[PDB]
Length: 21
Image 1: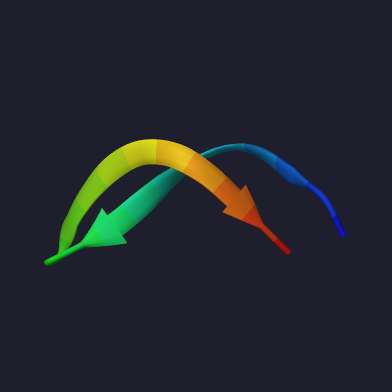
Image 2: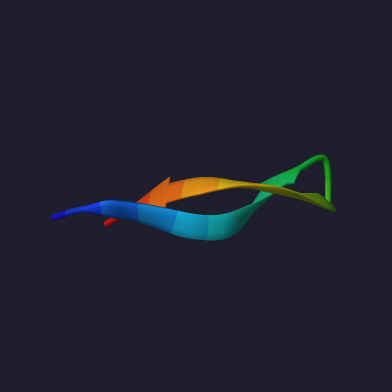
């Protein structure tokens, strides 16, 4: 597992962030 560059998804509105998986 690691966290890198990504795009969130709050209220069907993608918003640049970090995602871990």
